Length: 17
Image (cartoon, rainbow, N blue to C red; front, side, top):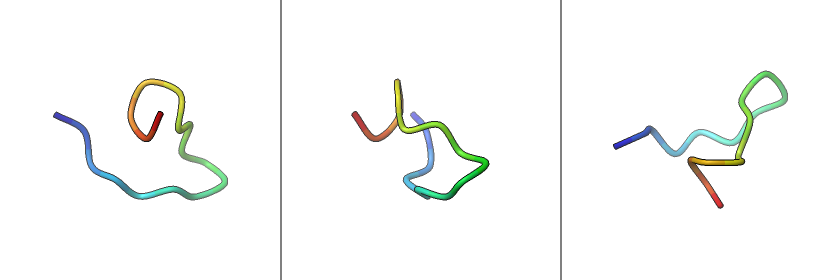
């Protein structure tokens, strides 16, 4: 269970996908 926070240092592959 990951936090949904889409930013330049965050990677969406595996969390917000």
